[PDB]
Image 1 (cartoon, rainbow, N blue to C red):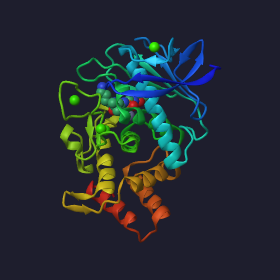
Image 2 (cartoon, protein in one colour; image 1 turned 120 degrees about the vertical axis):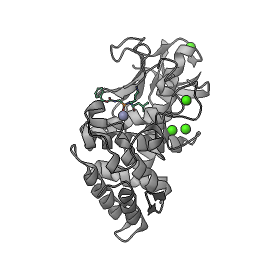
Image 3 (tube, rainbow, N blue to C red; image 1 turned 180 degrees about the vertical axis):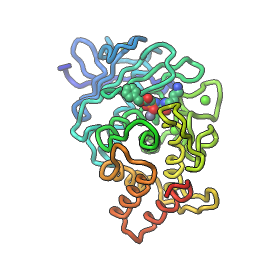
Image 4 (cartoon, rainbow, N blue to C red; image 1 turned 135 degrees about the vertical axis):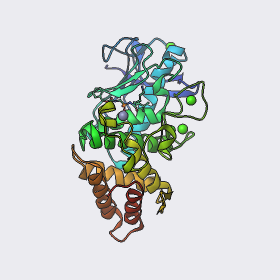
Length: 316
Ligand SMILES: CC(C)C[C@H](NP(=O)(O)CNC(=O)OCc1ccccc1)C(=O)NCCCCN
Ligand SMILES: [Ca+2]
Ligand SMILES: [Ca+2]
Ligand SMILES: [Ca+2]
Ligand SMILES: [Ca+2]
Ligand SMILES: [Zn+2]
């Protein structure tokens, strides 16, 4: 909408107060004009019609319980935009500052979030498995990263290419969580998962097997559920990424860690310069080796550690 940029204040899903960029024209709208061609947050009103209504508020204060998922979807989209711009010199998901749109309050009891080809969408959860999913900064960044992938490598959402697609979203979701630096970890979705159980998460990158996901190519799933296990076999690549950053010895193979920033540079370059819609795990290894070679040199520790990490997870 046309209006003037304003700054509202509200409370997110976890009860924390934050400022949000809004736009005033009769109402205050969740429209942040400070980033690219805008970040826009919509109310889906418990229905499945998208996007719903651009979020309108009478007084620029967002402390109602119903407001909390919108506050966080809007704010964390801003953090994710900032990460891509400041760290990778990428302007929004398409590289040309496309408007970023999210809808909250999607459906009833909806234990998921997704990119629908055009926008982000967040359920409220059923209160048992999830609380409103925009409360997780790693979740928000996971979803926006699907848009980045779709505009760049274009990894098809099935089988190995789809597991790479998933892992890319978990990797950058985690790197955005570290960027914001509030309780960062290598777990996925812990802030919105199972409010009655402490210490768990949807997936672990540091130890995928904690939740039954494979941590070695020999343990990959090859059935048809979950688009050929895209959220399962992602564990193999998540483990490799964790090892590249943090190091460790895994199935007897020792990996020298090189840290998160270099992990992110290597995988961002792989995603945007080398991967294709049909890349498999072996082709990802080659892309990551080439990316590290471009950035750090063929004889570098970074290249050697990429090779060790993929060796550790059984990917040649
Ligand atoms: C980070 C997690 C909290 C959320 C994360 N969701 P996602 O983005 O991977 C789901 N996208 C998805 O299907 O895209 C395909 C698609 C394409 C066009 C249109 C629509 C859908 C996820 O791990 N879900 C699995 C666990 C959900 C437990 N009930
Ligand atoms: Ca209000
Ligand atoms: Ca965390
Ligand atoms: Ca996390
Ligand atoms: Ca929990
Ligand atoms: Zn995903």
